Amino acid sequence: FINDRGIKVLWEEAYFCPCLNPDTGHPRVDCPRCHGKGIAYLPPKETIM
Amino acid sequence: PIQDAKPIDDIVDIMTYLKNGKVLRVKQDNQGDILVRMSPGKHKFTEVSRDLDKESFYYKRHWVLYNVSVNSLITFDVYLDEEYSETTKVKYPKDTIVEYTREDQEKDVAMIKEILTDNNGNYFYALIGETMLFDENKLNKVKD
Amino acid sequence: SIEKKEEVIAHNEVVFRSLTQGLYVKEVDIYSDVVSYTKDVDEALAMPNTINFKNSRKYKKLIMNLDLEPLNKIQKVIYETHLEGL
Amino acid sequence: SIEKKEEVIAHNEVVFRSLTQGLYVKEVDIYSDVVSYTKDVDEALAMPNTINFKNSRLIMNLDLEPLNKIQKVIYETHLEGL
Amino acid sequence: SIEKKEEVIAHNEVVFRSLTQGLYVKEVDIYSDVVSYTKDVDEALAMPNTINFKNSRLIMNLDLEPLNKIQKVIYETHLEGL
Amino acid sequence: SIEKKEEVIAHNEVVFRSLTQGLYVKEVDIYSDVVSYTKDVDEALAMPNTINFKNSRKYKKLIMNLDLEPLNKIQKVIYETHLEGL
Ligand SMILES: [Zn+2]
């Protein structure tokens, strides 16, 4: 049922980047893992949803 | 000849090198190049990196898990990361659609079979079905 | 008689030198080509190289220039405790 | 290699230590006789290491093992090539 | 064509330039010896171009290629027909 | 010895002239017929002609009058840098 009514979608999990400032607790403006957002992401997983 | 490429043929050799732990470089189509690696320690699993440059005090590679498909390895070209050459400065890449003229002044299409050069830097090209060498000007890059 | 020893890193940043001219870069243009120079290490186009700032993007064109020699400028402070008897 | 270096002596003191237990002195009484001991090397009771003080008051106990403590702090830089 | 025009000289200065590297001077030391160079033509170190200054201090280095820099700024109008 | 040159446009506006009278318009009535005149370019019924203000509507009746000669009054400032040697 789910595979039938769903749409193909890329699922990528979220995790806090190591680049977070240890003292303020807020992220670097630019880094490869996360582009200013304080949360990085894992490789995508193909999924129907 | 030129030493800028040494592709691996058998997937068995690829797996053997992965067991040894040496990094690999895996090309893609209209997409960024990939590095692949086997994780160390107790648990063995494949890891990948989107970065390509050599490790240094100012540059470190990032590794993450991924369910790499054997289809990619068997199909796509693979090299040893340490011994890979970034570019060979030639107009036409290897395995590229090209056009030429035969000995009887007949036009024909082909793909590049070999890329060669002399000691003075002049580049000669050999096409499929043509044993003789062709000048860079004599070839024509066919549009997709 | 070093009773105890400790080390600290104050700064760790990259600095570039021209191979032939022997000068250190200080400024670049919009295209990121060198505009100015100095013969002073204390005044240079420092690129941070701490743990967080690795794998930068601001100076990719500068790095690939063969005329430039990157240098890892690192500053340290080391504390040594001596016990010299009576 | 080294591009620039300088050495300075932040402190120079005399530390008192017991001969039997091996622990340094931490706290003392009115006459400066020992009431507490500590295993730390830095927190131990200490006095300036100059002749004037020594002439200005060893004096507390017969456990006669003072220890001249000297602290060296060094500033340096490197230019490590690629 | 031109209906009205006027020319004025906003600045008139002397620029210093190296003979070998070809880069102009940007920053200098206490004695005004060179410590920095720049490729820019306008940002380069410069001094007023008048005889009094010249007599009041070429003096810094043997790279004897100063450059008289003169800036012309012109105001004009046109009445272009149809 | 022009080391470098640059140009700037300060104003760009339209001004109208009577073919026979030689005067410049300054004022119009509700019907947009000419009411007044001047022999001074600095005081005229200027129509803006910058990039944004093209294809106006305020002066359509005025434009079609054959007795009037539109003129593109443009004001410029040009900076020239001279290097005259020693
Ligand atoms: Zn991050």
Image: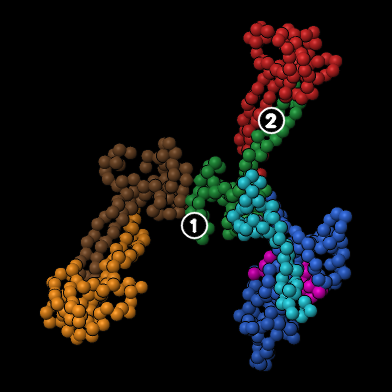
Chain colours: A cyan, B blue, C green, D red, E brown, F orange
Can residue B2 be seen? Answer: no
The type of residue carrying mark 2 is: Tyr
Give residue D68's quadrant in the image: top right
Q: How would you rate the neighbour count of disc 2 (Cα within 10 Å): few for under 14, some for 14-19, many for 20 or more?
A: some
Q: Which residue lies most toward the left here? A: F21
Where disc 2 sits, the SS reads: strand
Q: Would you say residue D1 is visible in this rendering? A: yes
Q: Spatial distance from mark 2 to mark 1, Cα to Cα?
A: 42 Å
Which residue is painted at 54% across and 49% down in the image?
C45
Chain of the residue that carries numbered disc 1 in the rendered image: C
Q: Which residues are magenta?
A: B71-89
The answer to whether marks 2 and 1 mark residues whose Cβ atoms lie closer than 8 Å is no
- Pick the front one: B133 or B49: B49
Q: Nearer the viewer, residue C17 or A15?
A: A15
- Quadrant into which the N terminus of chain F falls: bottom left
- Left or right of E62 on screen, residue F47: left
Density class for disc 1 (Cα within 10 Å; few <14, some 14-19, many ≥20) is few
Is D79 left or right of F16, judged from the image as shown?
Answer: right
Residue at (49, 59) in percent of width and height: C30
The residue furthest front is A1
On the image, which quarter does residue D29 sit in? top right
Q: Residue at x 75, y 65 (%)?
A: B25
Residue on which disc 1 sits: C29
The stretch drawn in magenta includes residue B77? yes
The residue marked by circle 2 belongs to what chain?
C
Residue at 66% across / 52% down in the picture?
A: A19
Vertical order, F53 against D51 (above or below): below
What amino acid is labelled 1 in the image?
Asp
Label 2 belongs to which residue? C79
